[PDB]
Length: 9
Ligand SMILES: *C(=O)c1ccc(-c2ccc(C(=O)OCC)cn2)nc1
Ligand SMILES: *NNC(=O)c1ccc(-c2ccc(C(N)=O)cn2)nc1
Ligand SMILES: Cc1cccc(C)c1
Ligand SMILES: Cc1ccccc1C
Ligand SMILES: Cc1ccccc1C
Image 1 (cartoon, helix red, strand yellow):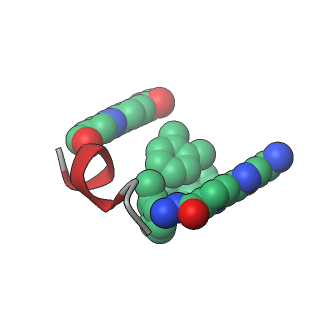
Image 2 (image 1 turned 90 degrees about the horizontal axis):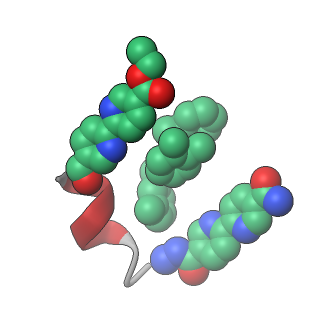
């Protein structure tokens, strides 16, 4: 999940 959201970065 963290990665899925942090892809913006
Ligand atoms: C959320 O964005 C998220 C959580 C966990 C994972 C993930 C990807 C790959 C592995 C892996 O290769 O584990 C080997 C033990 C684990 N967790 N991706 C995205
Ligand atoms: N928000 N994330 C990014 O902007 C981002 C773009 C690209 C990459 C990345 C990481 C690793 C590789 C590789 N070939 O191992 C390529 N691109 N990370 C983050
Ligand atoms: C998806 C992603 C972007 C930036 C940094 C990390 C660790 C993960
Ligand atoms: C499996 C994974 C997830 C998020 C960022 C980098 C990598 C190698
Ligand atoms: C999540 C991950 C896995 C393997 C190498 C680098 C990174 C950021």
